[PDB]
Length: 9
Length: 263
Image 1 (cartoon, each protein chain N blue to C red):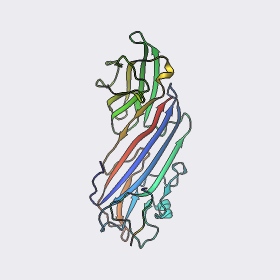
Image 2 (image 1 turned 90 degrees about the vertical axis):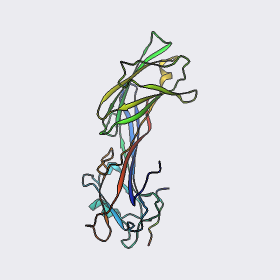
Image 3 (image 1 turned 180 degrees about the vertical axis):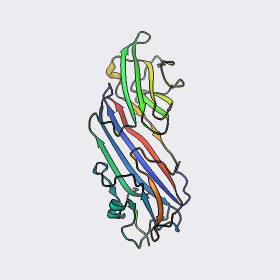
Image 4 (image 1 turned 45 degrees about the vertical axis):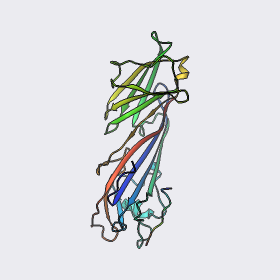
């Protein structure tokens, strides 16, 4: 899924 | 490929479905797009894309949908892909981040999403137990299409006879024959904005056996000023903190057929 990724920092 | 990334790579992928009647009347068409962001450099983590000033981001016919981590309101007012939380950052792990989707749909007789129009004509033949087929195609693309594949769902015994000075691409050749899939004829080039005919003779019991015909094309470009088929493009990439500070990047704009058929 290209549409699940988390914002980091 | 799994193409190379030198930091920030932006990909604009569009896919086109299109159904025509045999005579050429468009019955339907659907275009799905996405813009993805791959980053492999922690120094570029705090970037913001900005889309071409020529796109109407409020046009409801594109059904624009920003990923949830992205800030929908700066996108809508500014044409700027940015994070929902100003203090965070894109993953710098070279994963494909989906940041924006679109979907456009045309009704019958509407050719605005069609990159390649098609017509077919069939008449019974003298030289084979079957039909003389002509497939007329017109491109409206700025670039060329290479290795476009028409495919007719019959697996004849007698070889397909490609009428050779009546066809536009003279190295037009059968490249696959399968009991399941049918017969596939390759065409080497369809150049930008030009008309063409593929004409051939094929054994078949009756016209209906020759349908649905199917076509398959695909196109790419790593140019940084390239607009997608619908107009999508990246004006620049920029630092989250300082919108004046430009950042380095390549962009790939692509277009594939999916279900593209005459019926």
